[PDB]
């Protein structure tokens, strides 16, 4: 697969071509590097509504690599931020450093 491509998390190209046409839904997508080996680690996605304030929301049950994350209900802030994190299956304690994701403008409604 070309370069190694690390575990970076980016958003999804939404707009006038989002399959159906949700009035307020987001789409994410990330992927690690190399074909790794085994697994059983766990990856959660973080996303807070960048605005006057915020409480930062998290999400579990996320796979180390998502094809087309699908969120909905982010109506509250003008700009939304999102990060990524991973750890182990039965031996947590570090959770690694909250990898830096990115920030953009989700649905306008």
Image: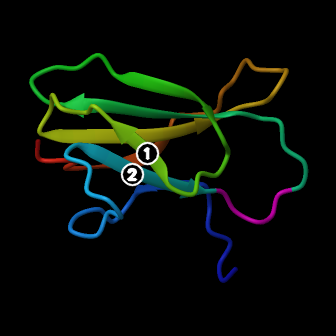
Mark 1 = which residue? 70
Query: Of the residues under marks 2 and 1, which one precedes in the sequence?
Result: 2
Q: Quadrant of residue 18?
A: bottom left
Q: Is residue 22 left or right of residue 89?
A: left
On the image, numbered disc 2 is attached to which residue?
27
Q: Secondary structure at mark 1?
A: strand
Look at the image and give the residue range highlighted in magenta.
32-36
Residue 36 position, x and y percent, is 82, 57
Q: Residue furthest front?
A: 20
Q: In the rendered view, does 82 fall on the left or right side of 22?
A: right
9 lies left or right of 47: right
Q: Indicate whether 13 appears above or below 96.
A: below
- Residue drawn 81% across and 27% down? 89
- Are the residues flagged by discs 2 and 1 in contact, CB closer than 8 Å? yes
* Image x and y of residue 43, in percent: 64, 36
Q: Is residue 33 magenta?
A: yes
**Percent position (x, y) of residue 93?**
73, 18
Task: Please name the residue shown 29% across and 44% down the image.
Answer: 25
**Which residue sits furthest right?**
38
Dominant secondary structure, magenta = loop
- The part of the image, by quadrant, that contains residue 24 is top left
**Closest to the observer: 87 or 59?**
59
Q: For the point 66% across and 42% down, which residue is it? A: 63
Q: Residues within 10 Å of mark 1 (few under 14, many from 20)?
A: few
Q: Residue at x 33, y 47 (%)?
A: 26
Q: Nearer the viewer, residue 25 or 97?
A: 25
């Amino acid at each position: 697969g070309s370069s190694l491509e690390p575990p970076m998390l980016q958003a999804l190209d939404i707009g006038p071509d989002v399959v159906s046409h949700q009035p307020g839904c987001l789409w994410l997508s990330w992927k690690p590097w190399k074909p790794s080996e085994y697994m059983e680690q766990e990856c959660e996605l973080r996303y807070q509504p960048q605005l006057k304030g915020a409480n930062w929301t998290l999400v579990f049950h996320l796979p180390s690599s998502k094809d087309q994350f699908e969120l909905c209900g982010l109506h509250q802030a003008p700009v939304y931020t999102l990060q990524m994190r991973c750890i182990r299956s039965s031996l947590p304690g570090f959770w690694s450093p909250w990898s830096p994701g990115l920030q953009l403008r989700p649905t306008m409604k």
